[PDB]
Length: 53
Length: 53
Image (cartoon, rainbow over all chains, first blue to last red; front, side, top):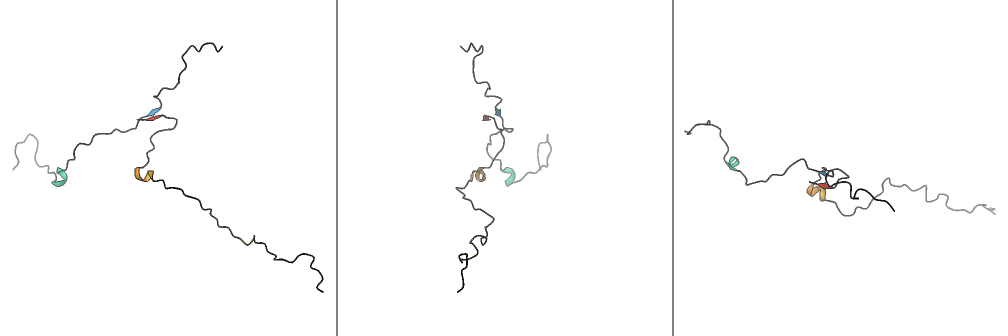
């Protein structure tokens, strides 16, 4: 009895459409940059220059 | 003399009507739940889902 199902029975819902992706991304750190904190930064010169006096 | 009192003499006022009940009912605590304080909670997903990416 029960005839034939024509299609192969299986779980209907795929794994996708059931996954939510976090809005953000992670990035790698690399070493700390602490020259500015110790000394500070001064913007005095201009580009395409050569020397500071 | 003194005839009979018909009813049996006794203390007139029952124990009830002389009791006041505190408005609150204490409860048992069980162990502390401190996962939220240490790590925090993020509500990102939705129900009927399966995975987080």
